[PDB]
Structure formats: C-alpha cells, structure tokens
Length: 31
Image (cartoon, rainbow, N blue to C red; front, side):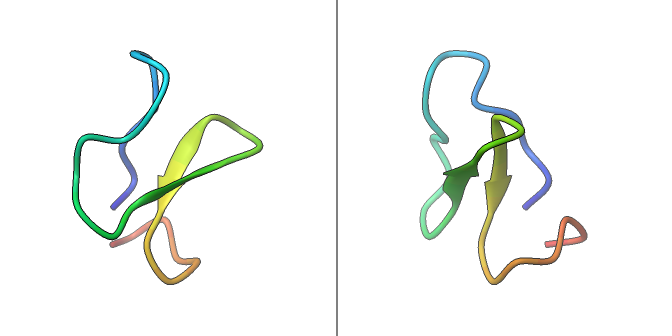
C-alpha cells in the first residue's frame, strides 16, 4: 500500500501513514 498521505492521511483501508508520509499496511511498501 505504497500510497502517500499527500492529503494528510491514507484513504485506503488498513493503510497507515508512516513518518515518510507514506502508507504502510504491514510494513512493506509493496502492499
């Protein structure tokens, strides 16, 4: 879930915003 929280937060479910302002589901960017 290598999406970015450009809007502020991930719109994808289960994806969290990591310090790099990037969504992480499990921890892998390739998700």
